[PDB]
Image: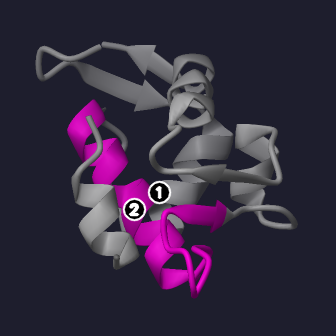
Amino acid sequence: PGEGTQVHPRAPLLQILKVAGAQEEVFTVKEVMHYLGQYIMMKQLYDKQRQHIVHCHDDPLGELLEVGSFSVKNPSPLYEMLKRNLVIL
Amino acid sequence: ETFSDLWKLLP
């Protein structure tokens, strides 16, 4: 979904975006990615030394991604999670 | 280098 597509995220993903500050029920994919970055940043999930690595184990984000960690340069787990967690409007 | 720099460069 790329063409400024409008989406409603499933409950578990929506809870995460609202923690990141989203006061919203409808998003574009771009807006979802914005709030995902916000979340990782504010919960400081990225590795301190190697900041492309995100440690999401023992966080609700890990529950959705289904991995303990991921690289932002290997973002497949993220896009897969979004395929499962976004309803197209 | 910074997570925020890296995140911005997501395809």
Pointer 1 or 2: first along the chain: 1
Badge 1 marks a residue whose secondary structure is: helix
Q: Position of residue A82 (x, y in %)?
A: 52, 28
Q: Quadrant of residue A21?
A: bottom left
Residue type indicated by callout 2: Gly
Q: Which residues are magenta?
A: A29-54
Q: Position of residue A47 (x, y in %)?
A: 62, 77
- Where is the N terminus of chain A found, in terms of image quarters? top left
- Where is the C terminus of chain A found, in terms of image quarters? top left
One can see residue A36 in this view? yes
From what the image shows, is residue A72 above or below residue A2? Answer: below
Residue type indicated by callout 1: Leu
The chain containing the residue under callout 2 comes to: A
The residue singled out by tag 1 in the image is A17
Verify CB contact (< 8 Å) between mark 1 and mark 2: no
The residue singled out by tag 2 in the image is A37
